[PDB]
Image (cartoon, rainbow over all chains, first blue to last red; front, side, top):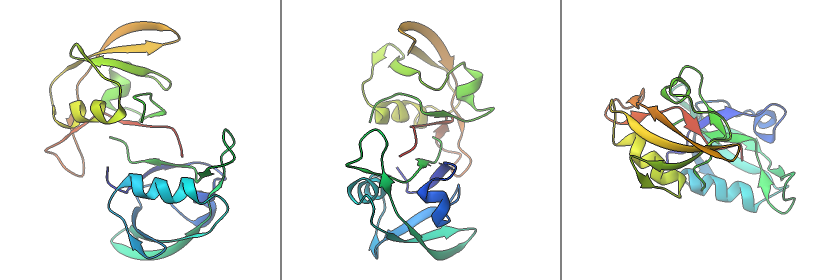
Length: 87
Length: 87
């Protein structure tokens, strides 16, 4: 639902780019997003390409760059190493 | 996508009711489900009431009961403590 992160995998693109549990993704490449599925779409469809994020963390919005890597099960789609917030 | 548990939060209603990573939820309250979002609908809309699950684990189905608790960020919605696998 909401574009807020649960757990971040160790040594993942998400960890390397500075994402943390609890971050809310505000925008990707300047495009505002409101749905987790939109964030997932940007990840899966852009393997190897940097994504410029604005995230809300601890009451402030800050920029990050994260680059999806080739998913080990299907190298044609991107993987960041993130799970959505627990529901 | 699939109602298959990638992550189960520690000390959550999900853990306390016996759910484990890798379980697939087959039905809730006798109603078959096929989508993660359907399980989320049952959880979010039934805070504080038991849900009767059938779960598939290692090829066998078994009954479990879980009781969603009031969500942290929003105490009007139920929370179980589940997330899909990393993406």
